[PDB]
Length: 370
Length: 49
Length: 93
Ligand SMILES: Nc1ncnc2c1ncn2[C@@H]1O[C@H](COP(=O)(O)OP(=O)(O)O)[C@@H](O)[C@H]1O
Image (cartoon, rainbow over all chains, first blue to last red; front, side, top):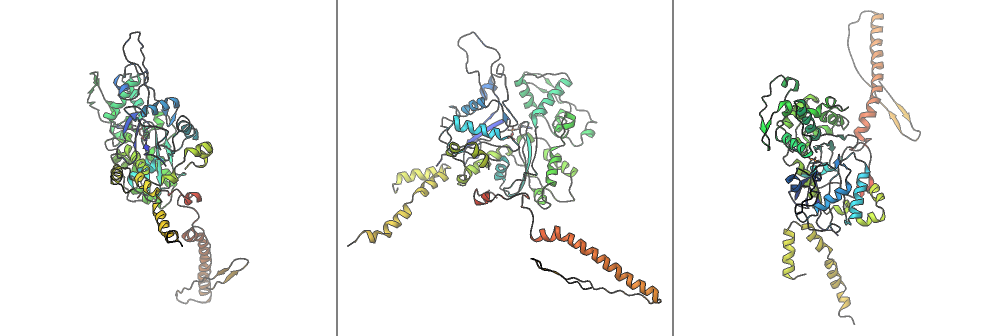
């Protein structure tokens, strides 16, 4: 026995949510809380001091933004409860919580303590009847409806590649990199001070993030493309100010393939990705050549998959046809896939009742992990 | 169960994307095996000398 | 050729193989043709003996895995309870 569950597609930057069997996440709001810088002695103005969404984005000025979650590992768990309480807002739910099944998201390569504390929240502070969350890549595959695939997510500062054969991942061939657009914008901030500009405020930095997402693409041959002169079509701020560009429009996003240039013993998404592919079956790579699942919204770049095709030619196999799946609802793919799963009578076997948590809890977490 | 207004609401609830809940509601009904038992032992129930 | 090896301590082993070939060359004398013919057969036998050793090498990797594989599709383990339930996603694609 249950109610209609809700799929909460936790984007590393923007969390999303929405009831079962639907097509579009009901809510789409980010992951940070602002608190006012200035206080007042005046009587009659606003209250709250904790805002997320249009309230925060509305009056960004005093609300000092702080991202509580880092690579899934959140440190403001209490504030996450407040965030989920905000998910239970009047404008948000007006529903109950201890009487409905739900669905959140889970990326791999994580400490169990996160799931442990999560169960503590939803089953100590809440009394959720049944709830089970699994690997996000399968949800993307649900959106595809394709047995095998190479899913690559793209969070704000989180990325990971997973190959799955008919609903079976490869634990010995799954990789992850701790970065996405987060340090890309931070690196753009670096470029800003490289040519003398600081955008040290939190909101200011998110504005920089929006600028990045607004004007950035991929180049063909980076060192050869460096030989030209960027004309820097200046954009003009909401404040009304000159915005130069530099190589940032193409150089800054390729930091992903130059972690040594940023200071990290890593190689590249496609590099370690194809390495894990090499660790897979001699035969399944053939399937994965056409089964290339693109996911995550950080992927929005001109010639993104095209430069990725160039990367494929860099890591060329022994002449075998390859194909990439590049949909348009890559962020929504996981939410919709969960909605598909949430629209299944198979969750009876795929769930864990709260009574099970009452009986064991931690042991149910360890044993009934997946 | 044969009341048309409740069945009407059931059809609209199905239409409201909650097909699983509505189907599960009627699968909860063991009226099928109940009535087959009714008529199974009914000649042993009724007309008993 | 002719091969017939057999082992039967708890397991049947019936090794039978051969190779039959023919060549031709013009007669010179006794010594030349002697070392010629025997050298040809000699190398062919040693050659095929080596081929048999490599055939054993082809057994371990091809033959076995051609019939009885060693690893799963994930090539690592088998969760029997996962087979007992969950319905892993047999209705996605
Ligand atoms: N124009 C754009 N170019 C590149 N990235 C973008 C653009 N617009 C939005 N994004 C990205 O969409 C991504 C959504 O990330 P997130 O919701 O954290 O993904 P995930 O669901 O993989 O965690 C963000 O990382 C943000 O940088």
